DNA sequence: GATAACCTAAAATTTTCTTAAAATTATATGGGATT
DNA sequence: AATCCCATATAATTTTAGGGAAAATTTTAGGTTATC
């Protein structure tokens, strides 16, 4: 429609076969517009300067670079649907955000081999968090995503062949409760269990107690449960991680990286295998990446000296 | 710009900063449009059926699958300019070519180690083609593209460090004759020389004779010269390889792959290093690829068995 | 007198070059358990 | 009595998901010359 908020509203109904988290996402952006000057402006009067200044206010509001850069993409697509409908001729969001803003994103550093051992040793000895020692060993040893872990049921483990069958994730959102989703990439993948993780899974099965009646979209007997008898979710693990890391840094001189969350374990897992010289496409299959490019980002850039040594070695 | 030919002529004049080879290529496609019924049609009367039926005629004419897919990309770009100028609404070339034609491209198989050994041995014993042994040894050992090799001069070799400095390519075309271009991507890169490549350049420098007065775009003293005293070109190495391979297959039971050309040397170089497990980003620097995806195609797909094996080795 | 090498013009083929959804994480807040 | 743990709603950040052809390389036809 005419105003920007109305154009985005039409763009949302146009492409409405989205998942619940996407619905929440679009809702968030829809509110930013309804509060920003850009929201009530006729799209036929939105120039390149108006869009760039919008990114500035977003920054002045407090939003991060990637948040604004993704919202810029949501709006850029909305203005391409209005051009495909002959409402304007030039997309005011077709510009590089790095020209208007500096990318001050926080670097996500994985754990060094030494940090990983200290961190693991602490969890194992901590009276409050040692119960989560298994899940963390499993995260560091498989690269699983947090909701991929939370979806693991009995029928997803092959202890005879020592394989993990990753075919889904368990999610939870306000109102809608729990649901099962597809990884979105089919996208199934099998992960082998090294000795350390093998024992970890076996210990979790043996120590499971108090699971309440719970079957969702055909899945039951989940491995990782909250104290309340229902399965764990990303929020539960993320919140626990935060308390654990703050507890660790209090008794250790060298704190853990500011970004030590459940995904840091995935990042650590991949970085280690890449630095150890693992086959790129094999690491890709294990990580479950759709594009080999995302996997290759974990590989340090090469230099002539770097390349020359590789050829002298081969 | 009513007819497709007029539209394409405008797209070429619009985007005019191109290199000579590009001019020839555009001219080739232009002749096709002039000889095909599609060329004389008004652009606002070209449906999605007209486009596919054009692909069928191109294939029936004999043009390869890749040739047609590239020409479709050129026409699709022209029709996206006509749409940006309020002339059409739907791009008739926005469709997958695999739905209309079968991709029957000849696979480009590299040389097995034994094939390479046999090929090299043959070249070194042939009275006619042994003078090209050094150049072919350099290709297999460096991965240079053919015109990158032709473009090499004395000021491009660092015998002290045993490095090759690739910064340009030497080309020739009917009319303009020789000229110096760029890798067209910082295409500059340094390739280390192994023992066999070092001795190879050493022989080419010592055995050089009869170079005629020649300097182009500031480059003189080229290493690989034709029997006429002027530098070699891709066409020169192309035709020579054609005879050389047709001669080899006459005296060996197992013929060389159909696509055994100067690029096949570059293909072999890359596959070998990739198969031996070279750092993928280091191999990219050597090959001169811009997108790591290009380098990654030389790596065989991974399966669960493949991935579990790597994870066991680590 | 045949072929094969070689050269070049013309033509062909091949190599090469995020238009956000959907997840994960941080935070404010409350009741209950711990030091 | 101050403090941490756990839980959940709300809000924010992060991870993840191709060719809008140019420019090269290769093939071939046709001719001369060297070779067998």
Image (cartoon, coloured by chain):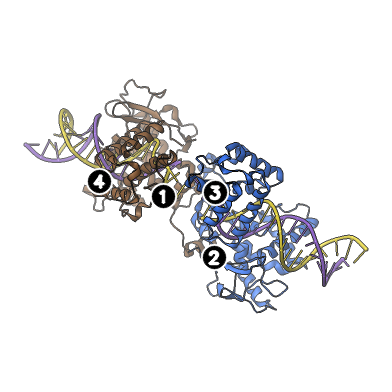
Chain colours: A blue, B brown, C purple, D yellow
Q: Which mark is residue A78?
A: 3
On screen, residue B246 versus residue B87, left or right, reads left
Q: Which residue is mark 4?
A: B248
Q: Position of residue B186 (x, y in %)?
A: 50, 35
Q: Chain of mark 2?
A: A
Residue B18 in view here:
no
Are dots 4 and 3 on a single chain?
Answer: no
- Is A128 in front, or is D10? D10
Front position among marks 4 and 2 = 2
Mark 1 neighbour class, 10 Å CA radius: few under 14, some 14 to 19, many 20 or more: many
Which type of secondary structure does the marked residue at label 1 adopt?
helix
Front position among marks 3 and 1 = 3
Are dots 1 and 4 on a single chain?
Answer: yes
Q: Position of residue A91 (x, y in %)?
A: 53, 41
Q: Which residue is mark 2?
A: A182
**Do residues under tags 2 and 1 come within 8 Å of each other at their CB atoms?**
no
Q: Position of residue B221 (x, y in %)?
A: 38, 25
Are dots 3 and 2 on a single chain?
Answer: yes
Front position among marks 3 and 2 = 3
Which type of secondary structure does the marked residue at label 3 adopt?
helix
Are dots 2 and 1 on a single chain?
Answer: no
**Position of A133 relative to A277 (above/below):** below
The quarter of the displayed image where residue B4 is located: top left
Q: Chain of mark 4?
A: B
Q: Chain of mark 3?
A: A
Mark 4 neighbour class, 10 Å CA radius: few under 14, some 14 to 19, many 20 or more: some
Q: CA distance from mark 1 to mark 4?
A: 23 Å
């Amino acid at each position: 429609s005419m105003t920007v908020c109305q154009l985005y509203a039409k763009q949302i109904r146009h492409r409405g076969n989205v998942k619940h988290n996407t619905k929440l996402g679009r809702e968030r952006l829809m509110r930013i517009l309804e509060q920003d000057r850009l929201g009530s402006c006729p799209i036929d009067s939105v120039k390149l300067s108006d869009a760039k200044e919008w990114a500035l206010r977003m920054k002045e509001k407090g939003l991060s670079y990637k948040t604004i850069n993704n919202d810029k993409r949501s709006l850029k697509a909305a203005f391409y649907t209005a051009i495909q409908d002959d409402c304007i001729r030039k997309n005011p969001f077709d510009f590089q955000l790095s020209d208007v803003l500096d990318d001050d994103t926080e670097p996500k550093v994985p754990l060094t081999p030494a940090q990983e051992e200290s961190f693991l040793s602490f969890i194992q000895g901590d009276k409050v968090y040692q119960k989560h020692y298994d899940a963390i060993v499993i995260l560091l040893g498989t690269g699983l995503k947090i909701s991929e872990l939370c979806g693991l049921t009995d029928k997803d483990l092959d202890f005879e062949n020592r394989v993990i069958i990753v075919s889904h994730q368990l999610l939870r959102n306000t109102g809608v409760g729990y649901y099962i989703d597809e990884p979105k990439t089919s996208g199934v993948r099998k992960i082998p269990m090294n000795e350390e993780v093998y024992q970890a899974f076996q210990r979790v099965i043996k120590n499971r107690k108090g699971a309440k009646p719970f079957i969702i979209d055909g899945y039951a007997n989940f491995l990782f449960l909250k104290q309340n008898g229902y399965p764990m979710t990303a929020v539960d693990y993320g919140g626990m991680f935060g308390r654990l890391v703050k507890k660790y840094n209090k008794s250790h001189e060298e704190a853990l990286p500011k970004t030590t969350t459940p995904h840091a374990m995935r990042h650590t897992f991949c970085t280690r295998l890449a630095n150890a010289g693992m086959n790129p496409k094999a690491l890709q299959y294990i990580m479950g990446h759709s594009n080999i490019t995302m996997t290759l980002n974990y590989y340090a850039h090469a230099t002539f000296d770097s390349a020359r040594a590789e050829m002298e070695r081969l």
